[PDB]
Amino acid sequence: SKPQPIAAANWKCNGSQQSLSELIDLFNSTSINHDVQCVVASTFVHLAMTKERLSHPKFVIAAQNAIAKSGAFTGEVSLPILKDFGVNWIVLGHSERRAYYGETNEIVADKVAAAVASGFMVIACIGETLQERESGRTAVVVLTQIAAIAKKLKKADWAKVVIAYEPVWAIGTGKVLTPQQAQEAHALIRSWVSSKIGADVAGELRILYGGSVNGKNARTLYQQRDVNGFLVGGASLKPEFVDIIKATQ
Amino acid sequence: SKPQPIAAANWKCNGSQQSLSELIDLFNSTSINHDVQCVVASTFVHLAMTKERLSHPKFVIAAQNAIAKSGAFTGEVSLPILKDFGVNWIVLGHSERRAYYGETNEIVADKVAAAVASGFMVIACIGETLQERESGRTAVVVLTQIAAIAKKLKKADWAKVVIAYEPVWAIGTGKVLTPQQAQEAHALIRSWVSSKIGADVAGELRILYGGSVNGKNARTLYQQRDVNGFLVGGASLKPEFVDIIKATQ
Image (cartoon, rainbow over all chains, first blue to last red; front, top):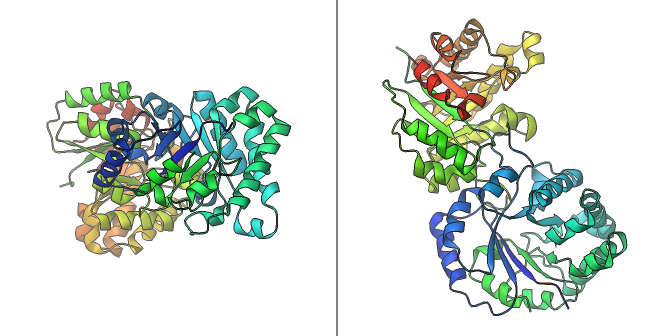
Protein backbone atom coordinates (compact mmCIF):
# COMPACT_ATOMS: atom_id res chain seq x y z
CA SER A 1 0.00 0.00 0.00
CA LYS A 2 1.29 3.57 -0.67
CA PRO A 3 2.35 5.54 2.42
CA GLN A 4 0.14 8.54 3.52
CA PRO A 5 -0.08 11.07 0.66
CA ILE A 6 0.83 14.77 0.95
CA ALA A 7 -0.72 17.76 -0.80
CA ALA A 8 1.63 20.71 -0.14
CA ALA A 9 0.83 24.32 -1.08
CA ASN A 10 4.03 26.32 -1.78
CA TRP A 11 2.66 29.87 -1.75
CA LYS A 12 6.16 31.17 -2.55
CA CYS A 13 6.60 34.94 -2.13
CA ASN A 14 2.89 35.78 -2.49
CA GLY A 15 -0.30 36.85 -0.76
CA SER A 16 -1.98 39.70 1.10
CA GLN A 17 -3.61 39.22 4.51
CA GLN A 18 -6.95 39.46 2.70
CA SER A 19 -6.20 37.06 -0.14
CA LEU A 20 -4.61 34.41 2.09
CA SER A 21 -7.45 34.69 4.62
CA GLU A 22 -9.97 34.01 1.80
CA LEU A 23 -8.03 30.96 0.69
CA ILE A 24 -7.59 29.68 4.26
CA ASP A 25 -11.42 30.07 4.78
CA LEU A 26 -11.97 27.87 1.66
CA PHE A 27 -9.54 25.24 3.02
CA ASN A 28 -11.29 25.33 6.43
CA SER A 29 -14.61 24.71 4.64
CA THR A 30 -13.29 21.81 2.50
CA SER A 31 -14.45 18.23 3.15
CA ILE A 32 -11.42 15.86 3.01
CA ASN A 33 -12.55 12.25 3.35
CA HIS A 34 -9.35 10.32 3.10
CA ASP A 35 -6.03 10.25 4.91
CA VAL A 36 -3.78 12.96 3.39
CA GLN A 37 -1.38 15.33 5.05
CA CYS A 38 -2.08 18.85 3.73
CA VAL A 39 0.68 21.42 4.10
CA VAL A 40 0.57 25.19 3.67
CA ALA A 41 4.02 26.81 3.25
CA SER A 42 3.44 30.60 3.65
CA THR A 43 6.02 33.39 3.65
CA PHE A 44 7.56 33.98 7.09
CA VAL A 45 5.51 37.18 7.51
CA HIS A 46 2.24 35.19 7.14
CA LEU A 47 3.04 32.33 9.54
CA ALA A 48 1.32 34.01 12.56
CA MET A 49 -1.96 34.63 10.68
CA THR A 50 -1.91 31.19 9.00
CA LYS A 51 -1.34 29.44 12.40
CA GLU A 52 -4.19 31.44 13.92
CA ARG A 53 -6.67 31.08 11.04
CA LEU A 54 -6.07 27.62 9.54
CA SER A 55 -7.89 25.24 11.74
CA HIS A 56 -8.58 22.26 9.48
CA PRO A 57 -6.82 19.34 11.37
CA LYS A 58 -5.57 17.72 8.17
CA PHE A 59 -3.44 20.82 7.54
CA VAL A 60 -0.07 21.71 9.03
CA ILE A 61 1.85 24.89 8.42
CA ALA A 62 5.43 25.03 7.00
CA ALA A 63 8.20 27.51 6.40
CA GLN A 64 9.67 27.89 2.86
CA ASN A 65 13.34 28.14 4.04
CA ALA A 66 15.55 28.62 7.12
CA ILE A 67 19.18 28.75 8.16
CA ALA A 68 20.50 26.30 10.74
CA LYS A 69 21.31 28.60 13.65
CA SER A 70 20.37 31.92 15.16
CA GLY A 71 22.95 34.72 15.15
CA ALA A 72 24.30 37.59 13.10
CA PHE A 73 22.47 36.81 9.82
CA THR A 74 20.49 39.94 9.04
CA GLY A 75 17.32 39.18 7.03
CA GLU A 76 17.36 35.40 7.67
CA VAL A 77 15.20 33.12 9.84
CA SER A 78 16.66 30.17 11.78
CA LEU A 79 15.35 26.73 12.74
CA PRO A 80 15.27 27.52 16.48
CA ILE A 81 13.16 30.62 15.77
CA LEU A 82 10.66 28.58 13.70
CA LYS A 83 10.65 25.78 16.33
CA ASP A 84 9.95 28.32 19.11
CA PHE A 85 7.17 29.67 16.90
CA GLY A 86 5.49 26.25 16.66
CA VAL A 87 6.26 25.66 12.97
CA ASN A 88 7.29 22.01 12.56
CA TRP A 89 7.32 21.52 8.81
CA ILE A 90 9.74 23.09 6.33
CA VAL A 91 10.48 23.12 2.59
CA LEU A 92 14.28 23.07 1.90
CA GLY A 93 16.40 23.24 -1.24
CA HIS A 94 13.64 24.48 -3.54
CA SER A 95 14.82 24.99 -7.09
CA GLU A 96 14.47 28.81 -6.77
CA ARG A 97 16.87 28.80 -3.80
CA ARG A 98 19.34 26.50 -5.58
CA ALA A 99 19.16 28.78 -8.65
CA TYR A 100 18.94 32.27 -7.15
CA TYR A 101 20.19 32.15 -3.57
CA GLY A 102 23.37 30.08 -3.71
CA GLU A 103 22.14 26.74 -2.34
CA THR A 104 24.46 23.92 -3.49
CA ASN A 105 23.75 20.21 -2.94
CA GLU A 106 25.85 20.36 0.23
CA ILE A 107 24.22 23.53 1.59
CA VAL A 108 20.77 21.94 1.07
CA ALA A 109 21.99 18.73 2.73
CA ASP A 110 23.27 20.62 5.78
CA LYS A 111 19.98 22.56 6.13
CA VAL A 112 17.99 19.29 5.85
CA ALA A 113 20.14 17.61 8.53
CA ALA A 114 19.88 20.57 10.97
CA ALA A 115 16.12 20.63 10.46
CA VAL A 116 15.70 16.92 11.06
CA ALA A 117 17.96 17.23 14.18
CA SER A 118 15.74 20.12 15.39
CA GLY A 119 12.60 17.88 15.07
CA PHE A 120 11.13 19.19 11.79
CA MET A 121 9.31 17.25 9.11
CA VAL A 122 11.25 18.24 5.96
CA ILE A 123 10.14 18.44 2.31
CA ALA A 124 13.53 18.31 0.59
CA CYS A 125 13.52 19.31 -3.06
CA ILE A 126 15.51 17.80 -5.88
CA GLY A 127 15.23 17.96 -9.69
CA GLU A 128 17.19 18.44 -12.91
CA THR A 129 17.48 21.38 -15.32
CA LEU A 130 16.26 21.44 -18.92
CA GLN A 131 19.88 20.89 -20.20
CA GLU A 132 20.31 17.92 -17.90
CA ARG A 133 17.00 16.39 -19.03
CA GLU A 134 17.95 16.98 -22.69
CA SER A 135 21.32 15.30 -22.14
CA GLY A 136 19.66 12.24 -20.56
CA ARG A 137 21.32 12.95 -17.25
CA THR A 138 18.19 13.26 -15.09
CA ALA A 139 18.98 10.13 -12.99
CA VAL A 140 22.61 10.95 -12.20
CA VAL A 141 21.73 14.58 -11.33
CA VAL A 142 18.80 13.84 -9.02
CA LEU A 143 20.57 10.89 -7.37
CA THR A 144 23.63 13.09 -6.79
CA GLN A 145 21.34 15.64 -5.06
CA ILE A 146 19.71 13.04 -2.89
CA ALA A 147 23.03 11.29 -2.13
CA ALA A 148 24.27 14.66 -0.73
CA ILE A 149 21.24 14.86 1.61
CA ALA A 150 21.58 11.16 2.56
CA LYS A 151 25.26 11.67 3.45
CA LYS A 152 24.25 13.92 6.35
CA LEU A 153 21.38 11.72 7.70
CA LYS A 154 21.03 8.51 9.73
CA LYS A 155 18.64 5.85 8.58
CA ALA A 156 16.19 6.67 11.44
CA ASP A 157 16.08 10.29 10.21
CA TRP A 158 14.23 9.30 7.03
CA ALA A 159 11.00 8.96 9.02
CA LYS A 160 11.13 12.82 9.06
CA VAL A 161 11.97 13.39 5.36
CA VAL A 162 9.75 13.74 2.33
CA ILE A 163 11.26 14.16 -1.12
CA ALA A 164 9.80 16.61 -3.63
CA TYR A 165 10.93 15.78 -7.15
CA GLU A 166 10.48 18.92 -9.26
CA PRO A 167 12.10 19.16 -12.70
CA VAL A 168 13.31 22.81 -12.89
CA TRP A 169 11.94 23.16 -16.43
CA ALA A 170 8.44 22.12 -15.24
CA ILE A 171 8.19 24.84 -12.55
CA GLY A 172 5.86 27.73 -13.51
CA THR A 173 6.29 26.92 -17.21
CA GLY A 174 3.02 25.02 -17.84
CA LYS A 175 5.21 22.04 -18.88
CA VAL A 176 3.98 19.21 -16.60
CA LEU A 177 5.75 15.82 -16.75
CA THR A 178 3.74 13.01 -18.29
CA PRO A 179 2.58 10.39 -15.76
CA GLN A 180 5.13 7.96 -17.25
CA GLN A 181 8.07 10.49 -16.83
CA ALA A 182 6.97 11.30 -13.26
CA GLN A 183 6.60 7.58 -12.44
CA GLU A 184 10.07 6.68 -13.79
CA ALA A 185 11.75 9.54 -11.93
CA HIS A 186 10.03 8.64 -8.66
CA ALA A 187 10.78 4.92 -9.23
CA LEU A 188 14.47 5.57 -9.78
CA ILE A 189 14.69 7.72 -6.68
CA ARG A 190 12.92 5.05 -4.60
CA SER A 191 15.18 2.26 -6.01
CA TRP A 192 18.25 4.25 -5.02
CA VAL A 193 16.85 4.76 -1.51
CA SER A 194 16.05 1.02 -1.28
CA SER A 195 19.52 0.02 -2.37
CA LYS A 196 21.65 2.61 -0.49
CA ILE A 197 19.60 3.12 2.67
CA GLY A 198 16.99 0.37 3.17
CA ALA A 199 13.97 -1.33 1.62
CA ASP A 200 11.76 -0.41 4.60
CA VAL A 201 12.77 3.27 4.28
CA ALA A 202 12.14 3.15 0.51
CA GLY A 203 8.60 1.79 0.93
CA GLU A 204 7.64 4.42 3.59
CA LEU A 205 9.24 7.41 1.82
CA ARG A 206 6.80 9.97 0.35
CA ILE A 207 8.05 11.15 -3.02
CA LEU A 208 5.95 14.10 -4.20
CA TYR A 209 5.85 15.46 -7.74
CA GLY A 210 5.98 19.25 -8.41
CA GLY A 211 6.11 21.35 -11.61
CA SER A 212 2.87 22.71 -13.14
CA VAL A 213 0.56 20.44 -11.11
CA ASN A 214 -3.05 21.66 -11.37
CA GLY A 215 -6.57 20.49 -10.52
CA LYS A 216 -6.92 18.97 -13.97
CA ASN A 217 -3.68 16.93 -14.19
CA ALA A 218 -3.26 15.85 -10.54
CA ARG A 219 -5.46 12.75 -10.40
CA THR A 220 -3.77 11.10 -13.41
CA LEU A 221 -0.32 11.76 -11.90
CA TYR A 222 -1.37 10.36 -8.51
CA GLN A 223 -2.46 7.07 -10.05
CA GLN A 224 1.23 6.24 -10.67
CA ARG A 225 2.58 3.66 -8.23
CA ASP A 226 5.54 5.73 -7.00
CA VAL A 227 3.83 9.14 -6.70
CA ASN A 228 2.77 10.11 -3.19
CA GLY A 229 1.31 13.55 -3.67
CA PHE A 230 2.38 16.99 -4.82
CA LEU A 231 4.28 20.17 -4.12
CA VAL A 232 2.12 22.85 -5.77
CA GLY A 233 3.17 26.37 -6.71
CA GLY A 234 0.83 28.54 -8.82
CA ALA A 235 -2.27 26.37 -8.37
CA SER A 236 -1.86 26.41 -4.54
CA LEU A 237 -2.92 30.10 -4.51
CA LYS A 238 -6.25 29.14 -6.19
CA PRO A 239 -9.46 27.27 -5.23
CA GLU A 240 -8.38 24.38 -7.49
CA PHE A 241 -5.83 23.45 -4.81
CA VAL A 242 -8.74 21.57 -3.16
CA ASP A 243 -9.15 19.48 -6.36
CA ILE A 244 -5.44 18.53 -6.00
CA ILE A 245 -6.18 17.37 -2.44
CA LYS A 246 -9.11 15.31 -3.82
CA ALA A 247 -6.75 13.83 -6.44
CA THR A 248 -4.56 12.05 -3.78
CA GLN A 249 -6.47 8.73 -3.90
CA SER B 1 20.80 71.91 14.29
CA LYS B 2 21.14 68.11 13.73
CA PRO B 3 18.14 66.41 12.10
CA GLN B 4 15.99 64.03 14.28
CA PRO B 5 18.20 61.22 15.65
CA ILE B 6 17.51 57.49 15.20
CA ALA B 7 18.23 54.61 17.56
CA ALA B 8 17.70 51.41 15.53
CA ALA B 9 17.75 47.91 17.04
CA ASN B 10 18.89 45.29 14.46
CA TRP B 11 17.88 42.07 16.24
CA LYS B 12 19.33 40.08 13.31
CA CYS B 13 18.39 36.39 13.27
CA ASN B 14 17.60 36.17 17.01
CA GLY B 15 14.93 35.93 19.68
CA SER B 16 12.23 33.69 21.12
CA GLN B 17 8.65 34.89 21.63
CA GLN B 18 9.44 35.01 25.35
CA SER B 19 12.76 36.84 25.13
CA LEU B 20 11.54 39.44 22.63
CA SER B 21 8.34 40.00 24.63
CA GLU B 22 10.48 40.74 27.75
CA LEU B 23 12.57 43.22 25.82
CA ILE B 24 9.52 44.87 24.21
CA ASP B 25 7.96 45.24 27.75
CA LEU B 26 11.16 47.06 28.86
CA PHE B 27 10.98 49.38 25.82
CA ASN B 28 7.27 50.06 26.51
CA SER B 29 8.20 51.00 30.10
CA THR B 30 11.10 53.32 29.08
CA SER B 31 10.80 57.10 29.51
CA ILE B 32 12.15 58.86 26.36
CA ASN B 33 12.16 62.62 26.86
CA HIS B 34 13.58 63.91 23.64
CA ASP B 35 12.75 63.63 19.97
CA VAL B 36 14.30 60.38 18.62
CA GLN B 37 12.94 57.88 16.19
CA CYS B 38 13.38 54.39 17.70
CA VAL B 39 13.30 51.45 15.32
CA VAL B 40 13.02 47.73 16.04
CA ALA B 41 14.04 45.48 13.10
CA SER B 42 12.84 41.94 14.04
CA THR B 43 13.02 38.77 11.96
CA PHE B 44 10.06 38.38 9.60
CA VAL B 45 8.56 35.68 11.84
CA HIS B 46 8.40 38.14 14.79
CA LEU B 47 6.84 41.11 12.96
CA ALA B 48 3.23 40.17 13.95
CA MET B 49 4.04 39.90 17.68
CA THR B 50 6.25 43.02 17.66
CA LYS B 51 3.49 45.08 15.91
CA GLU B 52 0.95 43.84 18.44
CA ARG B 53 3.09 44.24 21.58
CA LEU B 54 5.28 47.31 20.98
CA SER B 55 3.13 50.25 21.76
CA HIS B 56 5.62 52.97 22.67
CA PRO B 57 4.81 55.76 20.06
CA LYS B 58 8.45 56.69 19.58
CA PHE B 59 9.07 53.22 18.15
CA VAL B 60 8.38 51.95 14.64
CA ILE B 61 8.90 48.43 13.42
CA ALA B 62 11.16 47.47 10.45
CA ALA B 63 12.02 44.48 8.33
CA GLN B 64 15.69 43.38 8.00
CA ASN B 65 15.49 42.65 4.21
CA ALA B 66 13.07 42.20 1.29
CA ILE B 67 13.01 41.57 -2.43
CA ALA B 68 11.34 44.07 -4.75
CA LYS B 69 8.38 42.07 -6.04
CA SER B 70 6.12 39.20 -5.15
CA GLY B 71 6.31 36.00 -7.22
CA ALA B 72 8.11 32.70 -7.54
CA PHE B 73 10.88 33.34 -4.96
CA THR B 74 10.55 30.54 -2.44
CA GLY B 75 11.75 31.57 1.04
CA GLU B 76 11.82 35.35 0.32
CA VAL B 77 9.61 38.23 1.44
CA SER B 78 8.66 41.11 -0.90
CA LEU B 79 8.01 44.82 -0.38
CA PRO B 80 4.31 44.56 -1.27
CA ILE B 81 3.88 41.82 1.35
CA LEU B 82 5.55 43.98 4.04
CA LYS B 83 3.54 47.06 2.92
CA ASP B 84 0.27 45.07 3.12
CA PHE B 85 1.41 43.95 6.58
CA GLY B 86 1.80 47.56 7.79
CA VAL B 87 5.60 47.50 8.03
CA ASN B 88 6.91 50.82 6.69
CA TRP B 89 10.56 50.80 7.68
CA ILE B 90 13.27 48.52 6.29
CA VAL B 91 17.01 47.86 6.67
CA LEU B 92 18.67 47.14 3.26
CA GLY B 93 22.17 46.19 2.17
CA HIS B 94 23.41 45.16 5.61
CA SER B 95 27.00 43.98 5.58
CA GLU B 96 25.93 40.36 6.33
CA ARG B 97 23.75 40.34 3.20
CA ARG B 98 26.48 41.91 1.05
CA ALA B 99 28.95 39.32 2.42
CA TYR B 100 26.86 36.15 2.66
CA TYR B 101 23.80 36.52 0.43
CA GLY B 102 25.13 37.96 -2.83
CA GLU B 103 24.10 41.61 -2.49
CA THR B 104 26.30 43.80 -4.74
CA ASN B 105 26.25 47.62 -4.72
CA GLU B 106 23.76 47.52 -7.60
CA ILE B 107 21.49 44.90 -6.03
CA VAL B 108 21.35 46.99 -2.81
CA ALA B 109 20.67 50.13 -4.87
CA ASP B 110 17.77 48.46 -6.71
CA LYS B 111 16.23 47.20 -3.43
CA VAL B 112 16.56 50.70 -1.89
CA ALA B 113 14.88 52.32 -4.93
CA ALA B 114 11.97 49.79 -4.99
CA ALA B 115 11.46 50.33 -1.27
CA VAL B 116 11.44 54.11 -1.53
CA ALA B 117 9.01 53.82 -4.53
CA SER B 118 6.77 51.55 -2.39
CA GLY B 119 6.65 54.25 0.39
CA PHE B 120 9.14 52.79 2.89
CA MET B 121 11.55 54.66 5.13
CA VAL B 122 14.87 52.93 4.33
CA ILE B 123 18.01 52.44 6.46
CA ALA B 124 20.55 51.74 3.71
CA CYS B 125 23.83 50.29 4.90
CA ILE B 126 27.30 51.04 3.62
CA GLY B 127 30.81 50.42 5.00
CA GLU B 128 34.30 49.18 4.13
CA THR B 129 36.14 45.94 4.94
CA LEU B 130 39.23 45.62 7.13
CA GLN B 131 41.49 45.35 4.00
CA GLU B 132 39.94 48.48 2.54
CA ARG B 133 40.42 50.40 5.79
CA GLU B 134 44.03 49.17 6.02
CA SER B 135 44.70 50.29 2.45
CA GLY B 136 43.30 53.77 3.17
CA ARG B 137 40.46 53.23 0.73
CA THR B 138 37.54 53.76 3.13
CA ALA B 139 36.31 56.96 1.35
CA VAL B 140 36.36 55.63 -2.21
CA VAL B 141 34.67 52.35 -1.14
CA VAL B 142 31.84 53.89 0.88
CA LEU B 143 31.26 56.68 -1.66
CA THR B 144 31.12 54.08 -4.45
CA GLN B 145 28.43 52.22 -2.43
CA ILE B 146 26.41 55.34 -1.85
CA ALA B 147 26.87 56.55 -5.45
CA ALA B 148 25.26 53.23 -6.58
CA ILE B 149 22.21 53.88 -4.35
CA ALA B 150 22.05 57.56 -5.44
CA LYS B 151 22.09 56.53 -9.12
CA LYS B 152 18.67 54.90 -8.69
CA LEU B 153 17.03 57.73 -6.65
CA LYS B 154 15.58 61.19 -7.32
CA LYS B 155 16.51 64.06 -5.08
CA ALA B 156 13.01 64.07 -3.47
CA ASP B 157 13.51 60.39 -2.53
CA TRP B 158 16.22 61.27 0.00
CA ALA B 159 13.54 62.43 2.45
CA LYS B 160 12.86 58.64 2.83
CA VAL B 161 16.48 57.45 3.17
CA VAL B 162 18.72 57.10 6.20
CA ILE B 163 22.31 55.96 5.81
CA ALA B 164 23.88 53.50 8.24
CA TYR B 165 27.66 53.64 8.07
CA GLU B 166 28.99 50.38 9.52
CA PRO B 167 32.63 49.40 9.00
CA VAL B 168 32.49 45.61 8.39
CA TRP B 169 35.42 45.03 10.75
CA ALA B 170 33.57 46.82 13.59
CA ILE B 171 30.47 44.57 13.42
CA GLY B 172 30.25 42.04 16.28
CA THR B 173 34.02 42.26 16.84
CA GLY B 174 34.10 44.61 19.86
CA LYS B 175 36.18 46.99 17.69
CA VAL B 176 34.20 50.27 17.82
CA LEU B 177 35.40 53.24 15.74
CA THR B 178 36.84 56.13 17.72
CA PRO B 179 34.60 59.24 17.74
CA GLN B 180 37.10 60.96 15.43
CA GLN B 181 37.03 58.02 12.85
CA ALA B 182 33.21 57.90 12.98
CA GLN B 183 32.99 61.70 12.61
CA GLU B 184 35.34 61.79 9.58
CA ALA B 185 33.51 58.95 7.83
CA HIS B 186 30.12 60.57 8.41
CA ALA B 187 31.51 63.99 7.37
CA LEU B 188 32.88 62.63 4.10
CA ILE B 189 29.62 60.90 3.30
CA ARG B 190 27.66 64.10 4.02
CA SER B 191 30.08 66.23 1.91
CA TRP B 192 29.59 63.88 -1.02
CA VAL B 193 25.81 64.09 -0.63
CA SER B 194 26.04 67.92 -0.44
CA SER B 195 28.16 68.13 -3.55
CA LYS B 196 26.47 65.48 -5.76
CA ILE B 197 22.85 65.76 -4.66
CA GLY B 198 22.18 68.97 -2.69
CA ALA B 199 23.16 70.96 0.40
CA ASP B 200 19.59 70.84 1.76
CA VAL B 201 19.51 67.04 1.38
CA ALA B 202 22.94 66.76 3.04
CA GLY B 203 21.85 68.77 6.10
CA GLU B 204 18.62 66.73 6.60
CA LEU B 205 20.18 63.30 5.99
CA ARG B 206 20.48 61.03 9.07
CA ILE B 207 23.81 59.22 9.00
CA LEU B 208 23.86 56.55 11.72
CA TYR B 209 26.94 54.77 13.02
CA GLY B 210 26.95 50.96 13.58
CA GLY B 211 29.64 48.47 14.66
CA SER B 212 30.01 47.51 18.35
CA VAL B 213 27.88 50.40 19.66
CA ASN B 214 26.96 49.82 23.32
CA GLY B 215 25.44 51.69 26.26
CA LYS B 216 28.89 52.78 27.39
CA ASN B 217 30.31 54.16 24.09
CA ALA B 218 27.14 55.63 22.51
CA ARG B 219 26.98 59.06 24.14
CA THR B 220 30.57 59.97 23.19
CA LEU B 221 29.92 58.92 19.56
CA TYR B 222 26.68 60.92 19.40
CA GLN B 223 28.44 64.12 20.45
CA GLN B 224 30.14 64.19 17.02
CA ARG B 225 28.64 66.80 14.69
CA ASP B 226 27.87 64.42 11.80
CA VAL B 227 26.54 61.43 13.79
CA ASN B 228 22.76 61.14 13.92
CA GLY B 229 22.23 57.98 15.90
CA PHE B 230 22.99 54.29 15.67
CA LEU B 231 22.26 50.94 14.09
CA VAL B 232 22.80 48.48 16.97
CA GLY B 233 23.34 44.74 16.71
CA GLY B 234 24.35 42.76 19.82
CA ALA B 235 23.49 45.48 22.34
CA SER B 236 19.95 45.88 20.86
CA LEU B 237 19.00 42.47 22.34
CA LYS B 238 19.89 43.77 25.86
CA PRO B 239 18.46 46.29 28.38
CA GLU B 240 21.41 48.61 27.62
CA PHE B 241 19.69 49.44 24.31
CA VAL B 242 17.69 52.00 26.35
CA ASP B 243 20.99 53.68 27.38
CA ILE B 244 21.79 54.01 23.63
CA ILE B 245 18.42 55.74 23.16
CA LYS B 246 19.33 58.08 26.06
CA ALA B 247 22.69 58.76 24.37
CA THR B 248 21.06 60.46 21.30
CA GLN B 249 21.26 64.02 22.71
